[PDB]
Amino acid sequence: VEPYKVNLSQDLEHQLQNIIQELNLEILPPPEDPSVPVALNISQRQNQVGVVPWSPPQSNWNPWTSSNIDEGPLAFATPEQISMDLKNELMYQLEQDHDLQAILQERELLPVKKFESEILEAISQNSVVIIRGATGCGKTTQVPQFILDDFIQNDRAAECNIVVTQPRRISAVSVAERVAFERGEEPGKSCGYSVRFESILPRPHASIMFCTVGVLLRKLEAGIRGISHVIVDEIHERDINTDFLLVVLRDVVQAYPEVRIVLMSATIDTSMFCEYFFNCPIIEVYGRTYPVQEYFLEDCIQMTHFVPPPANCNLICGDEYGPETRLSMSQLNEKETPFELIEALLKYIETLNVPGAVLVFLPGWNLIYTMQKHLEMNPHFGSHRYQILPLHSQIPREEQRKVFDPVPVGVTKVILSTNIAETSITINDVVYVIDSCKQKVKLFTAHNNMTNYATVWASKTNLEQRKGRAGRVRPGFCFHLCSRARFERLETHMTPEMFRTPLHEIALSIKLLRLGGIGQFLAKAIEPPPLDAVIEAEHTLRELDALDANDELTPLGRILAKLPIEPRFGKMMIMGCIFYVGDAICTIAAATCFPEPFINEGKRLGYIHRNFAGNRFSDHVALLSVFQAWDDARMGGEEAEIRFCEHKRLNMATLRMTWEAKVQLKEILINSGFPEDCLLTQVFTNTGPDNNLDVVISLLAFGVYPNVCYHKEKRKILTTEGRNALIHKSSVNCPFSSQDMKYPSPFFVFGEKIRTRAISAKGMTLVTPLQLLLFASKKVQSDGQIVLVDDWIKLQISHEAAACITGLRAAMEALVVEVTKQPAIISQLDPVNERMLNMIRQISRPSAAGINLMI
Ligand SMILES: Cc1cccnc1-c1csc(C(=O)Nc2cc(Cl)cc(NS(C)(=O)=O)c2)c1
Ligand SMILES: Nc1ncnc2c1ncn2[C@@H]1O[C@H](COP(=O)(O)OP(=O)(O)O)[C@@H](O)[C@H]1O
Ligand SMILES: [Mg+2]
């Protein structure tokens, strides 16, 4: 499209030239001929292979707080006292609690129970152990208890502190709350969880800490201090952080052979892990399972006499089935889930007349919420006959526990669940399974910066373990919604995350923990990542100045490594602190770790939701506005909060988690030397002119880069690549069917590129051309009249202004490096550097680009 004109005032034009002359930067001269455009865009230490240090549990050391015990009963108490005190407390609890006895009886029926003696024997004599058994035997909930009680009953409760790693956030919290119940406790006594931005630490001795691997790695700066056993759960799922930890722990096992690693896996080939850990023993666990009659899409269409509404493996069909079964299946698009058939399959399950729950496997939040409303709109699937419980990570823990509840007699329990119900948790009374045969994976391509949340085909392993969910109670049934032809064009195993995930967050961990070369360390992985991913990670971190030319951790990189956030968002927060808008930026950063706090239900945003935006045309401004209004409503107590959150249609749980995350991000910046006065909550207006919010949007543009786009007409936008895309339906910038939005700038930075039959941009914020050139661009080529931004945008703007705004970028990044050496210096900055920040504040203003949002 034709270049967008930028109306820079003459006063601003000269101010930019002044500060560049004061900063001792030259204006790169124009090109001799417009044909050749000039580009305006402008330690000696090494590490060796070291091991993470280890030490066993002490009496006076708290492993969770990583501190000494000076005051309290266990201050200077002996290991022998503690051992008896905890034993006597447990032995008294068991005989005085008839409710705990009933629970302790349920435990001793679990298939894993009859292997207890063997597991304890293996772990006691061998460093590393693999506990292999079918999903639902009780590996996760019982093994850590067997190990703890074995030390308690034998008067060694002081010599036991267990770490249990889980792949998912909800697994670590659920299991903590479940094992707590199984000991008649709440989390905080002998059982605790530690996840990103949430923790209930357990007691200092005879304790189990359930956690995500990410948390554990961030706490290993000091080393594995005061831990006897490290249990790595659900290794078969091949979480990238789990794979990485197994590299770290194998080095720990070798240097400190007294430590006790315990790997626990579903029914897969564990030779790869066995060989990796020096041919360690494999304890086989198993209970009674029933043969499950497995059906494919052909069987499902024939048994139900189904007819769909008005390469592809549906066009291929077995010749042993009926003619109409062939013709019906043909009309089903395999890149959809057959919603109407699942509804018809539920009806068939009734006709069989054998009471049991139906576990439906769907990919992601989107298709489960679609399946739910689809059913409930049919009165037949009401409370009278049916109980439809959704099961994904983003549900409240109130509703996640309701899947385990028995239902009233003559009612069917249908679980619309994700891959969480595959191997992580087992549901009881499951006789029926409907497998969509799909997975939702986070595929990232760094060349165009596309976050592809794609629905892809599951493996034979997945189908085999999804089938196994039906055969725990009685002879079950599994309904695969994939052709017999498709089952052949399916892989044996899924691509492990290590092969298809960005490694820059693992690369910082490697350097922070001082484990040597990024490539050197990652070469020791059980299945090393692709070369191009390691090169990309090293390049990305060198660009941010997180690493130097020798690939060693800079003072900036050290901060980014300690922040549990995308390194680029980490740098955005550091810059926020220099501009004294740290709190706002910490809020924005935190918000990216949780779902949108707005309850939309799929439909476009109403008045209430859009009113938070103001005149800024920003989902990010809307989010900050919600937090300013919600934080005020909190002062009226817990009930006033619930009334505000329900009146405005906000997820109160999401706002609380985000705020707690913001406080923890703020905490790490303080500990890094940043002053508190640059992180104080500041009042702002989302309609009136506000210079603090102008800067916040500028630093936002830096953060989400290279997610920039240009608006065409209606919902159509063109991306960084120069390809057409759509404004997401959930955005405040998304118009209604008719009324076209007159945007005062066609430019937008945004959060992520959700791919669904097209390119859609979610979490959109309006930016001015000055912000584009300053923070939201790398390559800028000028021909004297027209500048070319990243070879996809042309601006009819002054050559001197473009070179000067590009000057400020380099000046700003130069200041960040100087600030990260001693963050205290942001309070007392050089007069020239304060004048450079004031000039960034100036071009941040809408007025500086000839725009008035009020009009
Ligand atoms: C609340 C508080 C007050 C003071 C200090 N710290 C915390 C805290 C918040 S979260 C947390 C944690 O996650 N600690 C933690 C987890 C894991 Cl998984 C292991 C180990 N111990 S170690 C390194 O492995 O020896 C330790 C501690
Ligand atoms: N929150 C819970 N509510 C009810 N039962 C549960 C809960 N968590 C686990 N269980 C039960 O514990 C048993 C084993 O669970 P788990 O330890 O996760 O097994 P594994 O890790 O071997 O697959 C199952 O019968 C399951 O139903
Ligand atoms: Mg398990």
Image (tube, grey):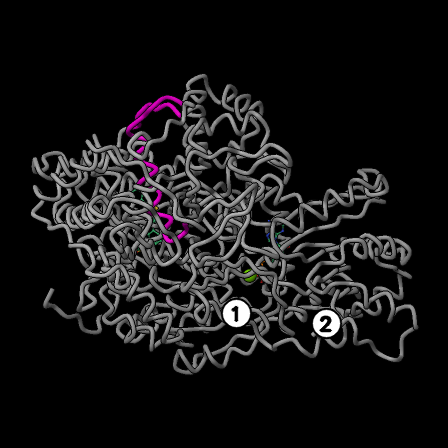
Which residue is at 36% across, 65% downward?
503
Furthest toward the top, the residue is 636
The amino acid on which the numbered mark 1 sits, given as a three-letter code, is His
Q: Which residue is mark 2?
A: 312
Q: Is residue 849 visible?
A: yes
Q: Secondary structure at mark 1?
A: helix
Identify the residue shown where x is 51% and y is 31%: 652
Task: Work out whether 704 lies above or below 37.
Answer: above
Q: Is residue 767 above or below residue 115?
A: above
Residue 676, horizontal then vertical, whole percent? 21, 32
Q: Which mark is residue 236?
A: 1
Residue toward you, 215 or 650: 650
Left or right of 112? Residue 596 is left
Q: Quadrant of residue 579?
A: top left
Label 2: few (<14), some (14–19) or many (≥20) C-alpha neighbours in 10 Å: few
Q: Is residue 439 left or right of residue 566?
A: right
Magenta stretch, residue numbers? 681-708
- Name the residue rendered at 21%, 49% in the picture: 803
Percent x, y for residue 147?
Answer: 45, 61
Name the side, left or right, on which 42 lies relative to 779. left
Q: Position of residue 626 (x, y in %)?
A: 45, 28
Any part of residue 88 in sight: no
Label 2 vs 1, first from the N-terminus: 1
Residue 682 belongs to the span the image colors magenta: yes
Snapshot quadrant of residue 854: top left
* Quarter of the picture holding the C terminus: top left
Quadrant position of ligand 2: bottom right
